[PDB]
Image 1 (spheres, rainbow over the protein chains, first blue to last red):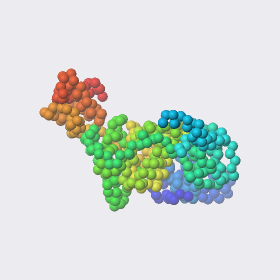
Image 2 (spheres, chains in turn orange, cyan):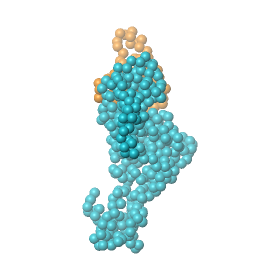
Image 3 (cartoon, each protein chain N blue to C red):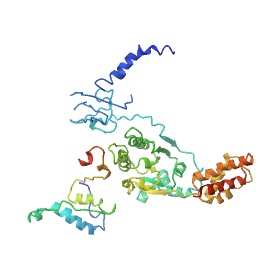
Length: 87
Length: 359
């Protein structure tokens, strides 16, 4: 449960509208989608330059729903013995 | 004395070889560079049984125990590459790395080959000289100096004597750590060496921690980022957890040196740690003149020469190329058989650099 809001980083409301729709809505209240029988999306593909809000709004989306932040670094996923990042 | 030490193998060494070998080798098994145990059953509490060799690795479960003095039997106990559970309190930190560490408090270097570098000093005046002198000024500014300072320029020039010139005005402690020597056969030498740098920086305030040749370490490499061993991979942890989180920005500072910024980890190049990028330019007509007049004090020359016209014919040059003008000036005097270098010797030394190189 990191501490962040959506007002700490502004101007991304255009991207936040797509994030809240694909993250906050299927997570917070799922009773609207479960009554229709459809399956809610568990994620959305994100891409962009560093510092553009991809990693800035990560803890923000986790703080709105009060979730644990787990970050997977790319250099940490490559090792010698089979294990580690695979686990 | 010669015959006295010969028979000690039958008398004194019999006890020494028993307590120093047989006890250490008991069961297919004081600086400790190695530890091994084979099939040891001890009732969770002081279990250990850790094989430092990459073959047949072991772990320790069933709770947590802290015994920094003696874990189980003493004797052979080690961590080395992979850190397992409760084995942390006794790391094998012994190593003759003292030849690598160079610590100079308040260096006396002012201007030798750095004459005319005051432009780069102004770049280091605000984010280095200012906090190391009056750190309380940043309280009213609202911001603080960035964590690290990145250096850039020609390879092997400007990253040595220019860093010590700033520490003179601030009376700080300059610690130079060579990155190529951080890489040894011991896995984790790069991360362990960085640990002791912040430990000594907390005792004495206003110290400068300098990392020489960071390209040999960086944030990741093949044997660590792409490999299974952890040395540089654990080195980046000491530059993040310690410096950023625990250590205040005013007293403790970090500076690197590199030929190219892309050779480092893009994770470190992001803001919050590495911000200031200092590019090393070349001395001007006034800067190159003050360097030649200093070298002329230790070299016999003519009293009627002029150092301004010597640096004028030579274009912008590095710190080494300027010292070459003075050293080669004595070579032309050998052909003329003179004890001192006249003005014509310096003119031929400049043309030797212009024509012989053409860079």
